[PDB]
Image 1 (tube, rainbow, N blue to C red):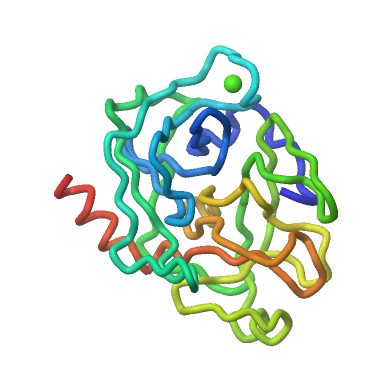
Image 2: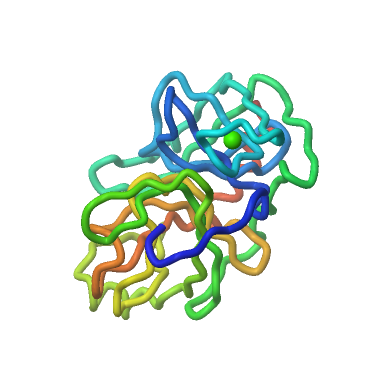
Length: 223
Ligand SMILES: [Ca+2]
């Protein structure tokens, strides 16, 4: 997260860190035993870390649980990032509490102009590199598709939306991928891609979760 702020410990209790010896992506807890993240985060050896603030210090509120199964969307296209979404089932149910909490899936989609909260432990610099150890947060509005496409020349699908600030300075970044975009109390986006971070006319691209709620619900029900 670039141009954001320190969330404050466990203030985003649905935020997870995916760890394969180190933090490599974010994710969102959607019930006690399932996390949703981005397909492009897919790898073997995933341990889900819940209740994290400082990802380099055991602070007392963590739960580490290994993934038992990962399910990349059937239609994930790594070339275009279309359908950039993945479900991870935990080996055991997390014990839910105020610092480890699920976030509601949307029943309807969000619209241009709505403010969202984006969070993660990704890069905080627009040029160069600095990785924070505590969770960072950013408030950003959903942009209209046409305004985003016109400004950025990005090639995006109806399964994606743009959020952020065309002037630059505030954006998600490398290492935030897979993490939550929450708008009006619902998980509407997953940090998916962009070009650089926080550059003028290059806003963040986010997987449009509302297009996948049928798939998420049926998949969890069957597994
Ligand atoms: Ca920790």
